[PDB]
Image (tube, coloured by chain):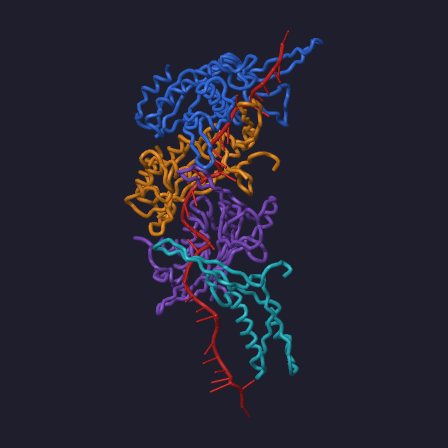
Chain colours: A orange, B purple, C cyan, D blue, E red
Amino acid sequence: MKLVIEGTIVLKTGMHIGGSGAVASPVVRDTLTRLPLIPGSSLKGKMRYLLAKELNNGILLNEPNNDQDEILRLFGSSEKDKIRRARLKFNDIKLSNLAELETFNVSSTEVKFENTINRKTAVANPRQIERVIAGSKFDFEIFYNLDDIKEVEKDFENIKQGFDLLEFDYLGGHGTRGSGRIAFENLSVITAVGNFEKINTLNEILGA
Amino acid sequence: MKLVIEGTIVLKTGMHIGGSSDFSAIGAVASPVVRDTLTRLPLIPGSSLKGKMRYLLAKELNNGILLNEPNNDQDEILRLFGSSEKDKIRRARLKFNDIKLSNLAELETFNVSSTEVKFENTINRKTAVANPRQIERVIAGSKFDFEIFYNLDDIKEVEKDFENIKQGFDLLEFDYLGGHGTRGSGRIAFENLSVITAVGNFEKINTLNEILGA
Amino acid sequence: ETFNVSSTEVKFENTINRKTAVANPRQIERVIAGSKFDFEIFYNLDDIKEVEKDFENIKQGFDLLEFDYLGGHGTRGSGRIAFENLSVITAVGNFEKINTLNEILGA
Amino acid sequence: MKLVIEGTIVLKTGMHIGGSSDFSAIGAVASPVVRDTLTRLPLIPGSSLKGKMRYLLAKELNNGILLNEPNNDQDEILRLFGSSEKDKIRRARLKFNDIKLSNLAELETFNVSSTEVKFENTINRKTAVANPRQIERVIAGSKFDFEIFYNLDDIKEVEKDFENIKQGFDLLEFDYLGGHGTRGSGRIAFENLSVITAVGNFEKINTLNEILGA
RNA sequence: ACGAGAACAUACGUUCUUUGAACCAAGCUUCA
């Protein structure tokens, strides 16, 4: 049995994922439709970092293969014997609200100008940062496959923990300097094929 | 008498199947996708699609787990994908073909290449430095027109076999096809799923084409 | 050789164990797609009352093979062929109805 | 878990910050203020607040002048605002956010525009002809809420960390925040410096709320 | 009236499992 967890990532401040024309530091985008994109690798990595740091005694210093059983069963592993298949399955997230952004007569991304005033020179050496704008939304869905009936409650508690841990941190790029602040909303879980018995408890421990 | 199931595998996110470290001096890009050797198109092998469908179907007929050898699968899985035992050896009713990229003209219409490169980190929690890694992927929205040959040898099993085939396609709808799929890539979807007959019309083809096109 | 490509390739396949989630690769030489093989098959005509049914069976074998593979790991991708330019010419002995075989095989 | 620093920065002098020379329409405004792009209202960047904040702490700890790059500042600043060494990178703990305007309605009650333009004349050499020019500031008295996030990674350092955050804010009321501030712009003042946490009430909130309420 | 007739080197097998493009950086300097 498999479950799908669907929500929205709304950008409270600007965001800037990725890099590598005649301009400095572009964002990583969709390659066909040129939409700004959250890579699912970046969302999975930041969620894994925050959830592994909170599901621990404070801080997190070891390799991702050496995490707790909840983290390793939620995000996968690669060992010579203790290899596990991940239960979460993240996806690349394209920009959903181009209609909402295009209503306000603003581009989906914009260029941020900022200096580095050297102290002994007091001269600007300016640089351009492309940022997808604030108020942008990103509809995601993560596929959760159910293997243990007695562990789906703890797995979903950890998933909600990772969500509201990411609500108090940023998502990629120059984050401490203004960028990256996100927030999660419209969080729900649905079943892929054939209804789970305990779906209401998951919608109420994930809808809070 | 033999049936053909034709459809399209559309890439919802990027898809990274395959790779040979090519001898040509390509430069400072690593980890390419498997390509067609003559027409220079990225390719979905039939072996990869067959293996992922077989794993998801053998996993789905479950209650318990899936941990066995492929030859000790469920008998419906052995009659769909074949088995090679010493005595209980069954011919595979399915024949997969290598799928190459179809809508190259439409990717050229939007003036963009057929495969792209995604830059990807791994920050080590000791040192907090990033080591960038180039992973060549196929652009999402690319379409891969496949055809699988179904040879029918028992009328009393074909409806259950196509029920299981549609279930395997549905299990691929909520999983990924090849490569770094847990990190975003690999997500596919099946479109235009239809069945046609090779030669000589099957009489009850409508129930197969309506439980495959559901 | 116009495309600066070899006559043959190599194809990589893994095998994911379901118990232990680990892949062991293997390699297969394949002759690449877009390769063409000009063939000629010789038929000797013992009896004219059976030649049309024989050629009907030969074309049946050819398109039956066109919906199957030709050797090797054909269930897992490879092997798919397509016969083209199928034509019949008589070698020795003038055969009075040769165009009917040329159309039952060339259809 | 984490504890945030809610607050409100207000302007006692018309503040100038940011800039662009756009292709579409310059208009009768030279060097405009940086503004938020969707909500179209002005914005203190978190980058600007971090840069001026760090420059003032650099004026505070090693006093007077420094003539030094900001990757080799004092070690508390390397822990707080972040640093990138050769391979042994010492990470940040202090995350700023793009500060945008909150009190739109109480300026709309008095029919006052959110931003301010002034006609800054310039008298040249003894020929003595005015050289008029227009700069765009934001009106003094406008309020700006901020929510600085603070990861707790040392229990026995958050005392000194919040005391030097208050020392930096205390050094920032006696300074401008960016722009043409040297000739009468940019002067700020802090108010309503309330601290709340994400969950719980651990790593005691009372001492930090008192040392930011001082 | 060919050391020859008959005979698919064929069957089962995911190039797959790990990982944030991060960190360092007042659009500022002289303008009645």
Query: Which residue does the image show at 34% across and 32% down from the upper left?
Result: A208
Q: Quarter of the image for the N terminus of chain C: give it.
A: bottom right
The answer to whether residue A189 is above or below residue B81 is above
Q: Quarter of the image for the C terminus of chain C: give it.
A: bottom right
- The image quarter in which residue A151 lies: top left
The one nearer the camera, B165 or C72, is C72
Q: How many marks?
A: 0
Q: Where is residue B181 in the image (x, y as percent from the top left)?
A: 44, 47
The answer to whether residue A64 is above or below residue D153 is below
Q: Position of residue A166 (x, y in %)?
A: 40, 33
Q: Is residue B198 visible?
A: no
Q: Position of residue A95 (x, y in %)?
A: 50, 37
Q: Is residue B146 visible?
A: yes
In the image, taking residue B22 as reference, residue A86 lies left or right, namely: left
- The image quarter in which residue A109 lies: top right
The one nearer the camera, B38 or B211, is B38
Query: Which residue does the image show at 33% across and 50% down from the upper left?
Result: A82
